[PDB]
Amino acid sequence: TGSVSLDRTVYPVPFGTIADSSKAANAAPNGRSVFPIHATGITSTIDSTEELPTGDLTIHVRINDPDFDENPAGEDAMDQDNALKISVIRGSDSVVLGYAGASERTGKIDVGGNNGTISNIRSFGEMDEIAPDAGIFELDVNIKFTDGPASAQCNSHDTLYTALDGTTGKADTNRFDDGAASGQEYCILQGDILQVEYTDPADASGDANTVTDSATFDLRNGVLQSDKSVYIIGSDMILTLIEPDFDLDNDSAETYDLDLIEWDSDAATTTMGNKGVTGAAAAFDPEPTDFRETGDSTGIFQIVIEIPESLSNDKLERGEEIILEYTDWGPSGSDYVGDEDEDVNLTIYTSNFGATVELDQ
Amino acid sequence: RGTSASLDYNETPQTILVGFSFASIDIQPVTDEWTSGQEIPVVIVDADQNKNSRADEDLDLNNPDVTLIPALRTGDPFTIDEGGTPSLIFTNGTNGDDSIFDTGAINNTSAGQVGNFTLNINVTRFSSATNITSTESIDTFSKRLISAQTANSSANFDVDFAIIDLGSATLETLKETVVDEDNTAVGFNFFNYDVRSLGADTVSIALLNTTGNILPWVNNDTRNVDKNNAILLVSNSTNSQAYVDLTNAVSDAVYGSTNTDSNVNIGFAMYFTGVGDLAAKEVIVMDFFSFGFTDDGVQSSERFANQIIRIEAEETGDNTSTFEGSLEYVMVNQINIQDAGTFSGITPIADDPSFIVIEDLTDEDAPRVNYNDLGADGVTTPVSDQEEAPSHSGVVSLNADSYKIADTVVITVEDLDLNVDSDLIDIFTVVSDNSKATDDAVGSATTQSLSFGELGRLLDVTFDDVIWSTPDGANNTATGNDSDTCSTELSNAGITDTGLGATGFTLVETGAATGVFVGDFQIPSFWCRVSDTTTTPYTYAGDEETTTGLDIEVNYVDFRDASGEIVEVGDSAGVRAN
Amino acid sequence: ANANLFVSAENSQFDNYMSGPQVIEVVVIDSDINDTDEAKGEPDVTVNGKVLRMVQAVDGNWYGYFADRDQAQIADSTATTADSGLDFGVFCASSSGTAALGFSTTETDGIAIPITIANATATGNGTQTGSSSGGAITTTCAANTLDASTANGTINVVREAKDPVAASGSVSVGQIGLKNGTANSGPNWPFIQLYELNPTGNVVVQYNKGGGVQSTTLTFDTVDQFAELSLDRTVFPRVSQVHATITDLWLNIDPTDEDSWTFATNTKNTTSSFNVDTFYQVFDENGASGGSALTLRTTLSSLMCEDNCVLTLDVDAQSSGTPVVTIQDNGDSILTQLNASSNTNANNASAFGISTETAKLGTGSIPVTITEQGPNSGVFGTYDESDKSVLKITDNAKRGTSASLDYNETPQTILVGFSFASIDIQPVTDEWTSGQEIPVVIVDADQNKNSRADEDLDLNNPDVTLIPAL
């Protein structure tokens, strides 16, 4: 019997960039699927150098079919045509991402399987066996924030759809078999169910059989953490960020700009990154230079930061209130990325001790 | 299989059985981890390839008799069969003056390497007075093209041209592997070809692009549908085996046409001399290679390494079915990622080939070698083996917690991924170039600015968290509180160790394959502090200060951590004084 | 362990392999037939079953030289001028031995004699150059070709053949009937008998004598697995001689002579017309004029040279503007600093070249000459009998900077560095009283610049930079 499995029970909602929207440049997302820096990092307009890269999450599909393991100690590939179907469902409406198992070919996105002709559907190619004696085939497929059912909640962004066929146009028909309904745009919302369809050519009974695995899209709040509350100026700050939705790929550890966090104190207010004030990023000397995820399937991001003795042309004082605030853009109450702009901050104290002065006599 | 002949002597006939054997390709690392710069044997046991019991049989792509060769590939390299089954023909005649084979030359010039291909055909004296067609076959793993044709070897036979079309392949099927070197941050294109079976004195290869059919070919004087249809790659090479770096002209010409890439086909051309005899079977192997990364290059989507590797296994003994080979792999680092020599220095076709690894390929993506085989039953079942090539977290530390003046500090860097050859001693020099932002840093002069810092920055030594650099360039004119310049002050103090480059501090590997690099230098009494690191060349302070009491810190830039990404690690120490 | 038959290619170091245009010397050192005054017979020596004509020399040993026909023809195709390069002389048909050499040579595939042709007919005279594509030869040679020769001794692959036994009474020249017996300068001796051999196929040399035959097996295949290059040390001081030991079987073309090869190793001379090349017998083994230089870069492919017959040199791996390796004139070379301008010095390796062959070995190109350590050892060295290397580390070399030398496509790095010394005074007892000579021990690897000789410190020697003082 064939079986299909997914890496994670839940997956984060993908996010796009400014170039994926036809709206004019704005200092705020204005409901778009954009993940920019905290307001102080943007100068009146969000451009390509001040937002996170494209957030197409890469889901890996795995099947366990010993029938396709024809070679016990050799390479095997699932060559059955269109045996795997990847689709996204939101209630009563369904959209299919593509087909797998046949030869890789160019195609558009079908909605609800309305297109009878299968050659017009995008094909991801034949899945490759993970190990010569395993029998499990894995295919890596990325899902864009546009690859979802049409809805009116996503009209806030005049989305530009990347073409999946040979044409270079950015129109809706280039990526999807049919244009979106007037007043609605293709997108993925919170709570949407991601499902994988695999048709086994031969089960234990040697006939056709359909198996399914499901995952749910979700968005979670972000919370900072530190190993301790007080810090000596110039010491090492183990800044730990625990937030699930940044774990886009379970097979690798991604990196994200430190600019998402901001320095807020009496000395200065800066994003502590390359987009901050002059001489800022040097003061902390990040190691690594950006937020780095602890493990490929953990979702926790950590980075070593040094407490600056001076932020920008002025020193940092003892007992100063240190505020580390970052904007999630994806809180629990957000239907999608860029809907709610909730911010979360952390309080950090500096070392205070008695500076007693004594004389010999 | 199974049909046999009976040879009889002394009225005791012996039966000559024909047959096949179950093979088993195995990769045996010398230890429990296949780290970079470690040549490990590859053992292939296949009695089908042992066709002579009194001699040694060596596998060869150029030998049509050797039907099956093990192969390894990563990414999507552009082989000869990416567009399906190709069509190859042979032609005799003259190229003429309006041809890229004669007028063209390798000079990285648009006119020099890109032009038009024209020819005239005189095949009346040939059999049937027609172009020499052939039967084309492709191997599933080595991707070798085997050409079957009439085995005419008469003295009057003379053939010069050879035109081959890659089935339905187009510029779209080529741009997935061939990348634009001008637009990508880091990217190189390589062309590997093997035409040794032809036995030609000189070999010339050109790339053809046209919106119509390749067979039969046309001429400029006949039609003007295509503005340009010839891109010269190899011109009169004396070696049939060559792995040459393509010039930027080829990459520009690939993207140099404004027409639709899907509406124009691609063709491959051959011109050679001294091939007046053709065997029954001929083999043509010529693929495209590509390596590099785009933008920040931290995610796996922007890291690509398209190559195909074939192992030339050699028989162990005269009558031993065990064929022995070996695999080499170098893990690319931040220093050699911008140098085309390290990509061109690998051997694609040899008994001990080498290949590039861009990411800590483990689990399902581990480097896997493929080898077809005819089993004892008679099916062509494949046998494959894989070995993980993970990365390691570089650790750098100093021998002591505190150091005196001229205490001869030594830097010990243990990271097995920087070993790029098990034979040669791996070394890393220090950059001495004021113009580049990586001045006085270990690495290479070439450097690109990214989100993780400088590409050419490998290791730095810092006093008081300030990089130790020698005053140079036009930004060292500051004199400070006095009228003496920092460089002049250091010269007066007698400190010839004005910087990292002055000391000659370089990283040298402990052994051939140890993977641990040892470097050392003496701490100077006086050093020149850098006023600001935000400009190149660095602007130095006008007065020197004594290094005692300051904390000496090193920073080894690790291009690939244990998970296979950039992690900044260093060690700390203090310059003691009494 | 043969008793009488000795073959040049027989070598346990290189496992009896043979490759390229090598001429193989066959000597039969037999005490039973060593005398040269009696009308003795020719010993029965055959290779692969084909008889090999033997000539008795003044030393009482019978000599015979053979080589592959295709390889010999391909090599002679590069002999633009006579007595230069891999010149095998003039080829003739196997049936022409009786008319030319005076004795039958039917059982061979062609003979290469050092004659020259004055009437170059298309039928009655051999090929002075030979077909570049190889294959069988049908051109015949006759007595009139001998009588019309204007220069005898064009063969340059066998240069030290022994003098044939002079004719006297009942004994003919070589006891087999050579017309002219002048060795190394005549038209008959030496001459090579060509044979058809198969690459990767064994070659069996046979000597038939009473009481038991003696047979030697040689393998005729590419020998790249044995071509290796080694350096005497690992770290090299500022001025130390750079010694190269080239253990290559293929380079031993002449068995009876020490062989000299010249290479153009400049890997960064980006001139279009210049390419890395190899040359044969530019200089003699004594450093004299060895003849003209001829191209071999485009011919090595057909000469069984799989990445084992080319030399290229890298002088600055890091391209830091500090050259590391340079070249000099030696006793086995005639190198000349063409760029004698006072602005530059001996460190500019591109300033050196060869006057006679400036066309390809001119300024730049780094002309490098190597000579064999022995006539038939198959091991070549840059260093001469005076220990003066062809390569030096530059005196102004920056510490840490290294150069790499390339042979067999196996780079060899030439690092630059030093070692920690320790000078110690060890008295014979617990007190250093007057009139007691006590040893002084200095351990310094920097001053040990030669691994095959004794280095003595000297104030008068500028090379000895550092001397202890009190």
Image (cartoon, coloured by chain):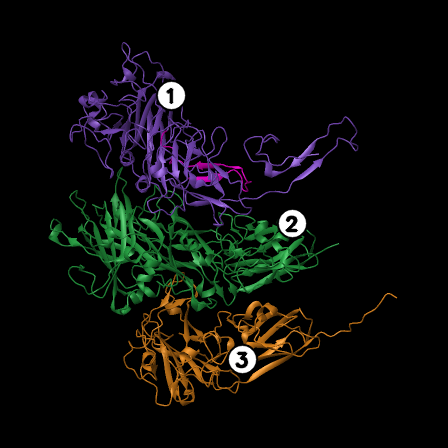
Chain colours: A orange, B green, C purple
Provide residue B128's location: percent of width, then percent of height. Answer: 11, 53
The residue labelled by disc 2 is B492
Quadrant location, the C terminus of chain B: bottom right
In the image, is B459 to the left or to the right of B14? right
Q: Residue flagged by tag 2: what amino acid is it?
A: Asn
Q: Which residue is mark 3?
A: A38
Q: CA distance from mark 3 to mark 1?
A: 95 Å
Q: Nearer the viewer, residue B82 or A48?
A: A48
> Mark 1 and mark 2, same subunit?
no
Q: Quadrant of residue C375?
A: top left
Chain letter of mark 2 equals: B
Cα–Cα span, label 1 and label 2: 76 Å
- Closer to us: mark 3 or mark 1? 3
Any magenta on residue C236? yes
Query: x%, y% of residue B405?
Result: 69, 52
Q: Amino acid at mark 1?
A: Ile
Q: Is residue C24 magenta?
A: no
On whether disc 3 and disc 1 are found on a single subunit, the reply is no
Q: What residue sits right under mark 1 in the picture?
A: C29
Query: Percent position (x, y) of residue A281?
Result: 57, 70
Element assignment for label 2? helix
Q: Which residues are magenta?
A: C227-254
The residue carrying pointer 1 sits among few (fewer than 14), some (14 to 19) or many (20 or more) residues within 10 Å by Cα, namely: some
Image vertical order of residue A295 relative to residue C326, above or below: below
Is label 2 on the same chain as label 3?
no
Q: Is residue B530 left or right of residue C24?
A: right
